[PDB]
Image 1 (spheres, rainbow over the protein chains, first blue to last red):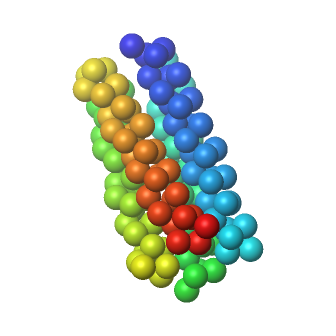
Image 2: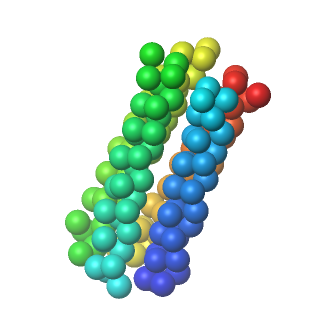
Image 3: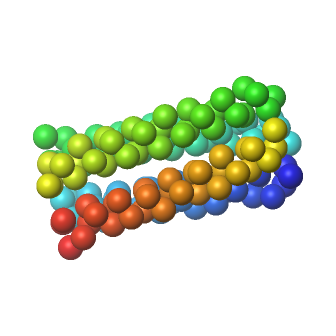
Length: 31
Length: 31
Length: 31
Length: 31
């Protein structure tokens, strides 16, 4: 249902942390 | 509910800005 | 509603094209 | 409906594999 959608969206909002920080890995290889 | 899903999707559609621009950071280190 | 969620998910499934191809920009700068 | 949303979210949770591994492509070009 809606509860087990809301708590996928809060997995995606983990993936969009690990997007940011595993880019910021690459950027801080490049400064 | 559906309102507080719709307004996660419009957080994701912020993350997919910061995807693009913090890639375009890396690409403009690389031209 | 559900129709205007489904057609955000099919924006995200555009962003996850432009993820892939604007990475594949960087990778083809790096081969 | 909700079933064919849940099974988009489990496409996105494929895209957020291919995010990670096609970054980890770039990082392992850069070590």
